[PDB]
Image (cartoon, rainbow, N blue to C red; front, side, top):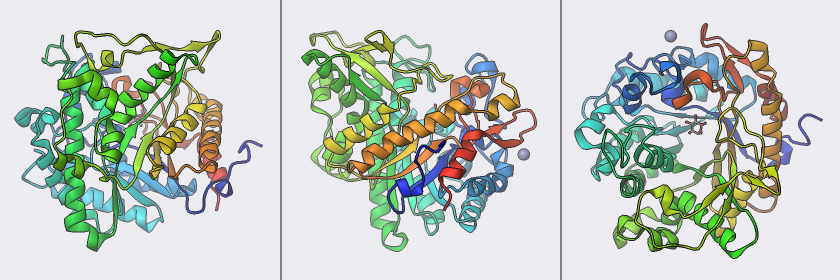
Length: 472
Ligand SMILES: OC[C@H]1O[C@H](F)[C@H](O)[C@@H](O)[C@@H]1O
Ligand SMILES: [Zn+2]
């Protein structure tokens, strides 16, 4: 049967199912309703930066249509909705003056979700630093971000926290560090060779440290000022793609483990254990910032749950560890990516070239976190796959590959949960086709099709799959 034995009965009691978007990717009204620009507004308006020179000015226009989209998610039997608050929609300059019109939007959205029985899971940050903070402070290179972020978070807790009980601070700080400061392909476009300046060997580590310190500061403020009255929770969202040793050799197994540590351990070892991974300390040395004992104690235990964004898996091949002049966070891992084993690719690709369909990577990642980090509460905060540009409406709707994707990946998640993994929820990326960053509107991740000419929504087969699987 097309559900493949899946239903709410196949998951733990009270397990949360939801869909996910982010502010810049779906809201539109980017320069309206009082919103100030983010670093993504500037980046996307520069010719050549995004496919088709497209941008999020209008996006899906969820800003005007949010009640349609909430009605849709309820009709599809979801329990929850993960979305983000745009920092610059609340504080156009990132600090100081509050944009009351922006505040009213999120109040209206939160209130409608609750009216319709959908639980809001709210991200404070999703790639969209206010441009004013980038220019005035240097963004995530500046340790002052901890204070700036805490003040923003404090405002959101005070204003929405009587209703919002499930918060996340950040989304994928690894990708900000990697693409923003190592490879220089996302804003602020910093890297050793880059026109904007930078240093691919140092800046990614500075940025990660500042995200951890900022997360910890915001959580400390929540716990000391707001938690007694509000009785909510705050976590963080981290990307994790699986790494599998190419062979059982000592060096291939070590390579795969080095990649896990440089990928997820970079954040989880501080958040769970209060220190960076030993291998990162060993290889990165004085380029890796040191937490003071006090900072380490603030960071440790500061996530009430761990959001994992999970998509794909890679084979890893090793090498003898070498003394090397530092060049980048990427080169620091000393690993070799391989995309086939025994003459077979690890999986077929979706539309995005990085996205190999490997359902067992979901099991890999979840099992790994369970066994290594004392089985922390995990929420799968994004998982999904994309269709290419230029299909007909009917072709978008008949998304049989995405149906197969969710069935297989959720079957693997079920396997990990049935073995004891403490997973509390699962969220599909995305509710809607939307603005896919460098790919603009050429990549379609939604379970609901969005016609970008007319802005009409049409549920795809995968939406109806969820509706059938999730019926109460
Ligand atoms: O690449 C697909 C998707 O991956 C992650 F979930 C990011 O948080 C999203 O912003 C992005 O659109
Ligand atoms: Zn509109």
